[PDB]
Amino acid sequence: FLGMPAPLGYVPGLGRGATGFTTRSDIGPAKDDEEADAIYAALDKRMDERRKERREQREKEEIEKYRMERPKIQQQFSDLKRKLAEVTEEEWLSIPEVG
Amino acid sequence: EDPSLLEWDADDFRIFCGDLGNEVNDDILARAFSRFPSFLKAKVIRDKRTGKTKGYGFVSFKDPSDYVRAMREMNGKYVGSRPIKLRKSMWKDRNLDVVRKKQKEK
Amino acid sequence: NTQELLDLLVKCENKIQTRIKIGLNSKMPSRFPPVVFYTPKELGGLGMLSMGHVLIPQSDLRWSKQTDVGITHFRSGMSHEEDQLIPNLYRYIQPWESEFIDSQRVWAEYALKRQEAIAQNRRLTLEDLEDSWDRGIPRINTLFQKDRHTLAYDKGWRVRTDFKQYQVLKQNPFWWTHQRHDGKLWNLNNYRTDMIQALGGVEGILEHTLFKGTYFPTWEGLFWEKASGFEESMKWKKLTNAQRSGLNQIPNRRFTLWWSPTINRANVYVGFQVQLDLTGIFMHGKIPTLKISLIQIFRAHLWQKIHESIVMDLCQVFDQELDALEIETVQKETIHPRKSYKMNSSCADILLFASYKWNVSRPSLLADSKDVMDSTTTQKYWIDIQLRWGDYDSHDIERYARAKFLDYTTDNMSIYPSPTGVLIAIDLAYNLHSAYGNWFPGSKPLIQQAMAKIMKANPALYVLRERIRKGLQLYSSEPTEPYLSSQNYGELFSNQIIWFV
Amino acid sequence: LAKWKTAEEVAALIRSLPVEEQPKQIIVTRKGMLDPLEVHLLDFPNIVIKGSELQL
Amino acid sequence: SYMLPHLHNGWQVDQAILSEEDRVVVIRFGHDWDPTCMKMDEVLYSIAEKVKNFAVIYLVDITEVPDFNKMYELYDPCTVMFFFRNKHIMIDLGTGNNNKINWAMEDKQEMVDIIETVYRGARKGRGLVVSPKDYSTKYRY
Amino acid sequence: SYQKLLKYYVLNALKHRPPKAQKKRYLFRSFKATKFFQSTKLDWVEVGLQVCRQGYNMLNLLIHRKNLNYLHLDYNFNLKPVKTLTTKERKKSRFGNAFHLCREVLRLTKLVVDSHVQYRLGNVDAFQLADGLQYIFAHVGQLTGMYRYKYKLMRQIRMCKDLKHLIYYRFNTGPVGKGPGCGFWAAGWRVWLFFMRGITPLLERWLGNLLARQFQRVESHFDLELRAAVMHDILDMMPEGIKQNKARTILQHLSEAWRCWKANIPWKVPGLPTPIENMILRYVKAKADWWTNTAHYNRERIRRGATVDKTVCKKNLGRL
Amino acid sequence: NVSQKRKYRQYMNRKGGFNRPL
Amino acid sequence: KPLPAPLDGQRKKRGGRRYRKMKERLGLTEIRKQANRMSFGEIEEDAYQE
Amino acid sequence: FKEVGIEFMDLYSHLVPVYDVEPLEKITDAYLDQYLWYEADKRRLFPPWIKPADTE
Amino acid sequence: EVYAPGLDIESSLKQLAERRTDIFGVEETAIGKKIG
Amino acid sequence: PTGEVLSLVGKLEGTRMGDKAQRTKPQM
RNA sequence: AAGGUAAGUAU
């Protein structure tokens, strides 16, 4: 039933009455804790910052070099979409629905 | 041996419903199946003690036109889990059995 | 000559063999026995002609025979030489230079014979020419064919056969020459016999093909239904795509069930053993075709049914001859329903209490003859029936009977009311009866005869055999109608109803 | 073509007759025509067809 | 171009699967921007016109509806769960996880055969059903 | 053994260039400075037993994270079922290959620590301690069988045998017996340390994944990109705020145009606007160029010898 | 020589006892 | 043109003579004559006669 | 003549054409080719040196 | 019809363009980049 | 040995092509 | 590592 609002106050997993599809263990996950998670994330970011700048610069240079050889899909018709709005309102209104 | 069936004999157009789940079949299911205004019958054969239905029920209507309409109206579609089957009730009483036995000669 | 050609053909032959193996089961067989891939389709196999050289192991070259006197064993490949190997294709292919030389010689001989017979006031002999049969690049074997006058009109069919690739949408491997035009140049008749005998003979091949699971000795004359009624129904019904695939996947299930013993071994498909839902068949590696075929054959608690049938037959036989056996009570315990297919016989099957005393000798097998009843004296006796499904390597009933008796009798979990008795075993796949343990005085031949008679015409066993025959599409050899009527003419009045038109 | 049509009529005669009254053994000396009759006899599995060495 | 109906809310997908009658509800979990998932969505779009009578396809986004990610272990792209007749069917096609198709089908006809087999199995009432084509091997050679 | 180890050394010597212009971010020092950890001093054997207990706790939580008692890991870091596991239970209790590697490496470190423990607590003398260290370092393949856990590790273990091959050869060169009395564990110890250093990023990444809460497409990708980009451009040009239905019908012409290119038949739609026709022409020319390119590329791949699927082969044949 | 009727156990759909009656 | 829903096959409620006439007109009568049975023993044809 | 359909068989190294013609046109062309071949062979219209020969 | 209405298709295309920045947005940041 | 079919190159020198190739006999 | 969970039925 697309286009309908979801009545709140009900858990979609429990209300539907489903069974846990336990495919395999160690494949799914199955405040002091928040502060510890933030501290560990900060430590991970500090560890990762050892090479971030040079890697990012090299990746940006490589992406820029790649764009010149072949740009994005919408780039090949940027001029066309620039001139696309020049069509009159009555033009696309009478577009033949038949194929 | 079935006095209730004699009381149910008032409605001629009797249909045999088959492939009924033990818990799927119920009076509410028969009421949902009672599309025609005529009085229905929710009787279904079931175990004497546990009440587990064997999957066969009989629905009686006084309108043969409603019988014909429901023959193709509710063939394969049923509210509960087990899909419904409809058959022309070949039910016979003991008198009919005796008459058939007598006439079996020719 | 081309080593690369040999290497590539062996490589793609192994590719197709592995494709067949993965079609059988997802995993890869540890041994992958070659009996399945080389048994001719007449005997119920793929019958893959190969140019390779694979030596058939001697362990799979043995076979058994459950004769009434005893269970005999044979080994076709017991010769003290190189291990038996399936012959390659080139071993029976005439060399091309040899083909040309033979063609020249035979055509010269045929021309000489025709010149000689021209003066004979008759056509060619066509009988003494049989010394030149199946020779020559041209169809000299077909030189006496009836359609030759029809065939003589055609000229230069080679170019037409070549352009048939542009005419026919399917590839034509035999574009070098047309069949029935240049004749069957390659004689491939001895190849089938050589392959079947080098695989261990007909009996050796059939030893691993559930053939012993059918009581009828249909060694010759049996009919194998290539197409069943379901095939006709699918052809007539104009089935959908999935239904078409299901109908086409029928013969695979057919011969995979037909090849169950050699395909469900222990050395082959190593891994976790598993038995079916309510039967006593152990399968190594999940094989959906074999699993579905087995659960069809053993549908509706067939294992419990055959166990009850055999125990009831044994009880009736014992009760009938209770006089000489001094049988006071012959009963059965309250056996748990699941104890029929259980691995260990914790609950005894049949109990037999005599009057005062019962002399029992030392445990042994039914093939033995000596007996010393003074070994033990007990007032009770137990009989156990072991329903087992023999594989291609675990079909040794006698060894299995000995091991099972030793394990079950000497075990804490197993509870037997009497310490003296005999355990019987029935190999369903082998259809072989055996027993091991003590015996009642003078009952050993009685028990042997009873087992043979029951296994001959047991109801559930006969139903299982019929189920196997239907599932494998091996129709029983057709009987011969009494086309004779000399005895029928005298017995015409004996016939209830008869008519002639 | 006549033999094929005769086989249909042959089975029709057995079909009209009761199973017990139908010939248990259809002894026809025409071995060539026996097979279509035997094929026709497949419509009645209970009945059997046996070759007739003696020819009426 | 991913014009199939999509569940904006997680609970909407739940009631959409619940609101089924004699039809199979193919809920394709994943993300439209993924390339393999884009191929799967294109295949589903191609199938949708031919089998719309009994097969309804209703896509969903894991980010939009993360509550069902842990319910059926949704941690791969291209996942498909044939949640039919309010019962998660057991579709076996020679794979370890016989309740999830997590890769785009090579051919549309194969997917049509699979979905019609699923419909037949669901109508028969069985909770499990096998596939005529095993996918333990990709037939690469 | 000498030739193989020389091969390994020369391959190590070939590829040797560090791009690693790091910022000297000492992650270990930062973890030390973290308030969640503290510093102290203790004996090495105490630290070893602490690490063994911590690894046992790690494996215990990793196993019984889903409240599954089917699989049990012994104190010797050997997993074992508590009974005959059911097939469904066997599928439920399954772990990845990297978990096999983690259990194996924890087993190795635990056994080394326990060997030092039993040495310290009297028992066997130090000479045999060194000999057992040498053996374990050069027999991990036999001891743990990392082969299945990781194929590459086989290389390490096999070369360890090679170094040991030389070590024993020299140790037993003369008057020294030809027995098992060889004590030069450092040679394989360094190799195992290097391989562990290489491996540990994978184990750390997977352990972080668990600790967190989130525990043929190229041609299809380009086709989807083309169609989605053209649809988005149309919806930008076509005022979706006013007209809604016809836009979907627009896609039809797209497909029509595409097949009109495939059939090589004339395609003229006077009803459609001229700029729309130009955009369709650009789309169809790009699609045709890409389609021909991939068609001939897949044909070349098939004819070269590359393995292809049946559906892919049929599609390539149709395109050709 | 005669054979009295043969009896059998009704293991299926029997709630009287877990073990088959004897 | 959506494909028809593969509903489970329903047999004929009552076999009629007109239905039998269609069965007589269309069926597998000729296919049943050709027996697909294969002898267990080897045939005289080659392995790949086809 | 009518429209002869053209399909392609993939020998995995190239595409070989196959052409489906009208059955009446097909049989007429077959008879034409057979007659031409017989008349050419009966008059030695083709020299022996052409490699494809029915003799060998 | 089986397919979603025009508004839903437009919303889906806008979401795809916003998420997949390879062929949409000012710059190509990443496949799953929230901001291009 | 049963695992796979061995290459012919190893046993190439065992015998010759058509070593046991016998001609056919007429029927009836 | 795996490619080896039958489904159904109410507790």
Image (spheres, coloured by chain):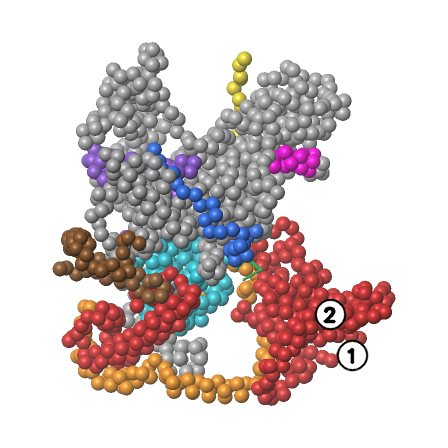
Q: Quadrant of the C terminus of chain B?
A: top left
Task: Tell me the blue chain.
Answer: K
Query: Circle 2 is placed at which residue position?
Result: F164
The amino acid beneath tag 1 is: Lys
Q: Colour of chain E?
A: cyan
Q: Residue at x 60, y 66 (%)?
A: F151
Task: Tell me the red chain.
Answer: F
Q: Colour of chain A?
A: orange
Q: Is residue C408 magenta?
A: yes
**Which x, y percent locates residue F219?**
37, 71
Q: Distance from label 1 to label 2 (Cα)? A: 35 Å
Query: Circle 1 is placed at which residue position?
Result: F41
Q: Colour of chain G?
A: yellow
Task: Tell me the purple chain.
Answer: H
**Which x, y percent locates residue C273?**
58, 47
**Which is nearer the N-term, disc 1 or disc 2?**
1
Chain identity of mark 1: F
Number of on-image labels: 2
The amino acid beneath tag 2 is: Lys
Query: Is F152 or A95 nearer to us in this picture?
Result: F152
Counting other residues with Cα less than 10 Å from the Cα at mark 2, is it few (<14), some (14-19), or many (20 or more)? many
* Disc 2, SS: helix
Q: Is residue C450 left or right of residue F3?
A: left
